[PDB]
Amino acid sequence: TVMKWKTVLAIFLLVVLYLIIGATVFKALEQPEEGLQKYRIIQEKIDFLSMHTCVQTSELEDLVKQVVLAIRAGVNPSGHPSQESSMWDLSSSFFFAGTVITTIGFGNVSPHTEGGRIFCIIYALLGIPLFGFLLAGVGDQLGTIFGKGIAKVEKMFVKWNVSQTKIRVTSTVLFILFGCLLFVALPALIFQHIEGWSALESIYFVVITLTTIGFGDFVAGGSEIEYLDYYKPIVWFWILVGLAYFAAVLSMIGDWLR
Amino acid sequence: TVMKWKTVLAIFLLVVLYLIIGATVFKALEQPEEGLQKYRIIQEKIDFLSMHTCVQTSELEDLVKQVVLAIRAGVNPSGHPSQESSMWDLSSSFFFAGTVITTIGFGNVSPHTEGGRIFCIIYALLGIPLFGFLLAGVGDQLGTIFGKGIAKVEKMFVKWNVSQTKIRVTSTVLFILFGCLLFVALPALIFQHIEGWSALESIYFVVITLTTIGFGDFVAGGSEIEYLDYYKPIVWFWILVGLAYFAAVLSMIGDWLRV
Ligand SMILES: CCCCCCCCCCCCCCCCCC(=O)O[C@@H](COC(=O)CCCCCCCCCCCCCCC)COP(=O)(O)OCCN
Ligand SMILES: [K+]
Ligand SMILES: [K+]
Ligand SMILES: [K+]
Image 1: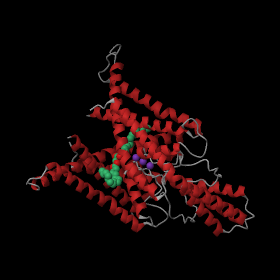
Image 2 (image 1 turned 90 degrees about the horizontal axis):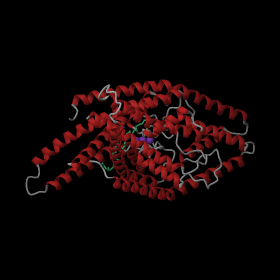
Image 3 (image 1 turned 90 degrees about the vertical axis):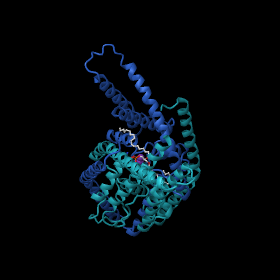
Image 4 (image 1 turned 45 degrees about the horizontal axis):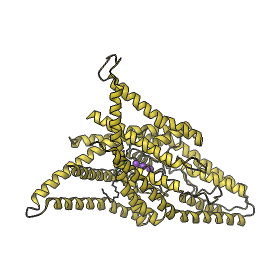
């Protein structure tokens, strides 16, 4: 039941127009913010040069170029590093490898050396099918468990016989809402307590992570706030559970369609 | 085809084991490099302060904090901006929207405004099922044409005393290798010509892009290289072609394996 050649062209045309609409609206939303940021940085640099007689713009440019190059490495220059705080923590390495197999790819931490890149390529290629098999198995198992639970929920007592599929739709909408409430809506509050993030920033981080976009501007562990009680393993297990459960819901929806 | 509970536990233990192994070896590979980086920037800052008596460590730290705040914004400080050129042009945001639906998410181009984050969430949730349906349709279309072509060639070819399984796995291996080399090795060469990146950097970028990891350390568009017109749309079409072909090949191999 493969799609018609002309049909595929219609979906492709729709995707292309979709992307054109998106590009125009991000352009119009987002150019003023970086216009003001460019103005702010150029005015700040001019004030710094004007106020400091001793400093030379060539030396300042060389120092800023070195600092931005350092940012690529991932080490923050603003704070003095103790050097018992290590970016590649066993916990951090576990979280990074988990994101690599999970295909999130935040990007705040990444391999830099030649072997690091080669091992990252090999590790991703070998790991991704394994995680895919795990997710498919957990999704199918959870789907069966959910369907038997659905049978238990449909007691058939005081149903009020309004419609045959009325309670099927009501149960599906209430389970999906409950799952979203616990998986996406509730962790956001934990994130607000732990890191003081805004509501939009936290909900955006959770959607980006569970949708496996992984922009990396917002990451679970950053800026030395001394997280406590095994923050990296619990958040990675959280990501696995959320991705699996929604993979199950999507698979069930597809089964219903078929 | 329900899976067993016992083997799910074993698979999860295997995944956790592999994660622990990877973390232990990554830590040992990667700590010395960043140790040297921290020492290098510490000694450079100390040398700078020693050279300039007038500058005061507090003002310099404040300046560094502002510069690293500006890096988050996405505007480079090293070069003076002409302002005729803008990061959020139609081509860059076309590529960005393509990455968002494609689930690459490089992260060098991210939305900071209140409206931008909300629209990014809505745009992702709307677009991703659409791209998923397009990829499934293209994958199955490629699979069907490949199946008919392989059946036709197999029927014409190998008439006399040859194992069918051997011929089938020879054909699949040769086809996958040819497609993989043409789609991955050749663009690494184009990237080598256009940019300063080494061969390992280019192959790493291509593997990270097609596999949907999207680390963002290396991206096709960067460093004010005055990239030729419509470079972002063509690279995005190449990304679409690579993902569709690889997904189709995986779909075919999986279906045949289960059949
Ligand atoms: C609050 C909202 C909640 C959201 C709901 C949850 C969302 C759940 C998941 C939704 C997003 C989609 C998940 C995608 C899973 C990624 C798995 C994967 O393997 O990546 C892609 C497939 O992987 C590949 O295609 C890799 C291609 C081959 C790799 C080539 C690398 C080098 C090869 C050299 C040798 C080749 C070795 C093997 C050759 C077969 C498939 O994803 P996609 O492209 O379809 O995503 C686009 C639409 N979402
Ligand atoms: K990603
Ligand atoms: K992904
Ligand atoms: K990513």
